[PDB]
Image (cartoon, coloured by chain):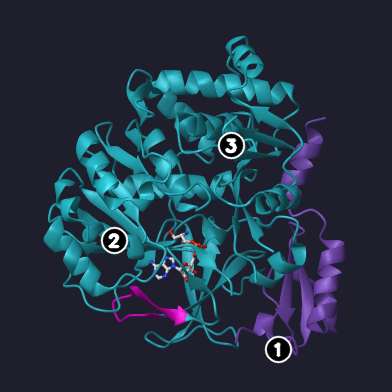
Chain colours: A purple, B cyan
Amino acid sequence: TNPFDDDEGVFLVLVNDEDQYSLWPEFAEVPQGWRTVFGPTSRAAALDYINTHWTDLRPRSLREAMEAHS
Amino acid sequence: ATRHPLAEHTLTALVDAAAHTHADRVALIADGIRLTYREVHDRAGRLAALLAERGVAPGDVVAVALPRSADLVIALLGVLRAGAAYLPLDVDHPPARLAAMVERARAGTVVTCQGALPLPGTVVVDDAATRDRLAGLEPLPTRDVHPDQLAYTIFTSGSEPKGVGVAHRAIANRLQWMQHTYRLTPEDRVAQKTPVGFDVSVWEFFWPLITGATLVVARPGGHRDPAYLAALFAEHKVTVCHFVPSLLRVFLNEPTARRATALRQVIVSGEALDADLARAWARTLPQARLDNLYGPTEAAVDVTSHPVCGAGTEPVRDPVPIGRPVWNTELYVLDSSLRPLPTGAVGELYLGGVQLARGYVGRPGMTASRFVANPFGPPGSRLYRTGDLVRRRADGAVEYLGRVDDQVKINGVRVEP
Ligand SMILES: Nc1ncnc2c1ncn2[C@@H]1O[C@H](COP(=O)(O)OC(=O)[C@@H](N)CO)[C@@H](O)[C@H]1O
C-alpha cells in the first residue's frame, strides 16, 4: 500500500519555490528544492493544512505573470 | 535520458501554424460535408470572438457539451483561441453529473446546441440570434497564451470525480512527440471515434490538425458499432486510429474489419493488451502497425509507447510491454520506502517531467497527495504516483503488472469502486 495513502503514517507538508505543495512521509529525506512548512503530524492534519493554505494551484510564476498583465 | 527541444510550447501555436500552412486542404470530413483548414479556423475565430465578448478571458475554463460533429471541433478550437481551457461534457452522462463538473471546475460558460440543451453562461451555437452574431463578428486573433495555462480539464472517476487540469506545455510535448514518432502527412486520415470525455480524444482532435492531415469524424454513437467503423474507415481510407483493448477485440470479431486496408498505424491504450489479441490484429490487418501506449490522465494522455506489430518488431509474448518513455518524461519504479528498485523487481510506477498535470481542480489536498516532491529530478520538481505495479525488463522496456488498489476499467473507462 502506498505510503502517501497510509492513514496511520507520520507526515510533513512541503512547499517548493513555485508555491506548490506536497504531502511527504517523515521517513523519507526531503528532496532538494522543497521546504518543510508543517508537521510531523497525522495524515489528516497535514491534508487539512494543505486544503486551507494552497488556495491557488497555479505555479507562482504563472500567477505573477497574470497579475502583471495589469 | 529523454530530453528533447520543443518547437512550440502551446497548442494554440501548433494549431495556428498548421492553419496557415494547410489553409486550402480539407481539415474535417464530418456530418456529410468537408471543411478546409481555412473554413474551420474562420468559424473557430468567430466563436472565440463571441466568447471574448461574453467575458471569456485567458485562464478561464469553458465547458463544451456538443455531440461529435464539426461544431464540436470548431468549439474546442474556439475555446483554445480565446485563451481558455475546455472542459468536455459527454452529452450521454446524466445532468447532475455534468452540473457538478461545471461547478467544481468553475466553468462560467457552457457551449452547447439546441439538441443537447436539456447552467450559467450558456452559448447555444445554433440558436438563430447566436448564428447571426457569429456571422457578424470578425474572427478573433489568437490570444497570447502562457504555456503553463491550462489547455483542458478532463474529469476522471474519484474514489466525487476529480478534474485533471493539463497545461498547454504538457499537451504540446505529447503531440509533438507523437508527430515525430508516427509522422502524419497531409494525406493521412485519423478517425475521431473516442468520446470527448476520455483524454485519448485530445490527440484524435489535435494531432491531425497540427500536421495538415484530415480528421474523419464518426457519427455520435458510432464507436459502439464495429461494422459502422469498418465501413467508415473503408469509405474515407482512414489511415490512423485508436482502440481500447476490449473494443479492439470487438472490432476484430467483426467480419468486415479486414476491409480497413488503408490503416497503416493503430494506437492501442487504456487497458492491458494481451498477446493473443496482438497476434489476431496482425493476421487480420497485416499492413497496419500496432503500438501499445500507456499513461494516466494526470500526465497528458500517454507517457510510454512500445511497437508491437509491424516490420522490425519482436515476437509478441505476454506481458506485452508498455514500453519506453516519451520526450521530456522520466519513469521510476519505487518501493514503499520510495527507493528505486533494481531492474526486474516489481514496484509502483512514478512519473516525472513536462507532461504532469497542474493538479486536480479545486482539490489541493488530493493534488499534494498524488503529485509529490521528486527525489530524483531537478530541485522543486514533482512526481505523479500512478497506482500501477510494473517492472523494467532487462532491455529497459517496462511491463504493466497490475494495480496497487481496486481501480478497474470497463470499456477503457477508469472506474473507482
Ligand atoms: N497500455 C496500457 N496497459 C495497461 N494499463 C493501461 C494502459 N494504458 C492505460 N492503462 C491503465 O489506465 C490507467 C489510466 O487511465 P485513464 O487515466 O482513464 O487514462 C488512459 O487510459 C489513457 N490516458 C491511456 O491512453 C493507468 O493508470 C493504467 O492502470
Read off the residue under disc 1: A27
* Letter of the chain that mark 3 sits on in the rendering: B
State the image quarter where residue B272 is shown.
bottom left
B30 or B203: nearer the viewer:
B30
* Letter of the chain that mark 2 sits on in the rendering: B
* Helix, strand or loop at mark 3: loop
B338 or B48: nearer the viewer:
B48
The answer as to whether callout 3 falls within 8 Å of ligand 1 is no
- Magenta stretch: residue B97 in it? no
Answer few, some or many: residues within 10 Å of disc 2's Cα (few below 14, many 20 plus, some between 14 and 19). Answer: some
B274 or B306: nearer the viewer:
B274
For ligand 1, which image quadrant applies? Answer: bottom left
**In contact (CB < 8 Å): disc 2 and disc 1:** no
User: Relative to B359, does residue A29 appear above or below in the rendering?
Assistant: below
The residue mark sitting in front, 1 or 3, is 3
Task: For marks 2 and 1, give the CA distance.
Answer: 48 Å
Q: Magenta region: which residues?
A: B391-402
Q: Amino acid at mark 1?
A: Phe
